[PDB]
Length: 129
Ligand SMILES: Cc1cn([C@H]2C[C@H](OP(=O)(O)O)[C@@H](COP(=O)(O)O)O2)c(=O)[nH]c1=O
Ligand SMILES: [Ca+2]
Image (tube, rainbow, N blue to C red; front, side, top):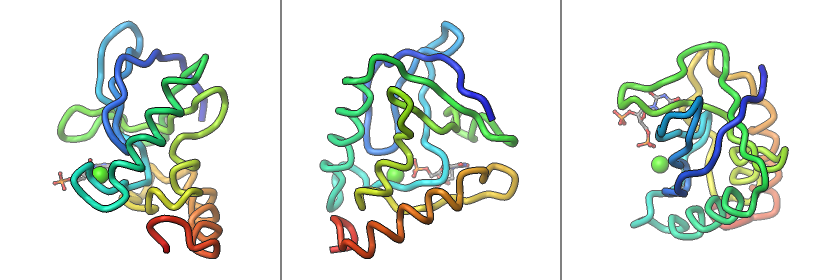
């Protein structure tokens, strides 16, 4: 996989942002994770964690996997990096997202993320508390 540029337009919630990609506004949905919706337990904490990470970043990058790049709602599907750190992984590692929506052929970083999840669960963080 390869990283590509984007800029933040607006943080939205635990697992979506509005990014400018190739000069066009798009909603992006994080691959391989699920955060609680804002109305749900740890929802606001996930939103805030994601927001801070992408707003504080000097450089945002998107990394598409090998399969589908947009979902049925027209959202981009990517791994999102904030100054080289994967937002997807960071949410999982803090117990603010579960590994989820693992579809065959768009699952390059599955094991990386499952490792993070196991460490969050061991530490009983947030969702796992
Ligand atoms: C993360 C992800 C979600 N989706 C679709 C499946 C789910 O469909 P449904 O809307 O029919 O449930 C929805 C979950 O996203 P959200 O967790 O953002 O709601 O988005 C994909 O199609 N591919 C993906 O990689
Ligand atoms: Ca969600």
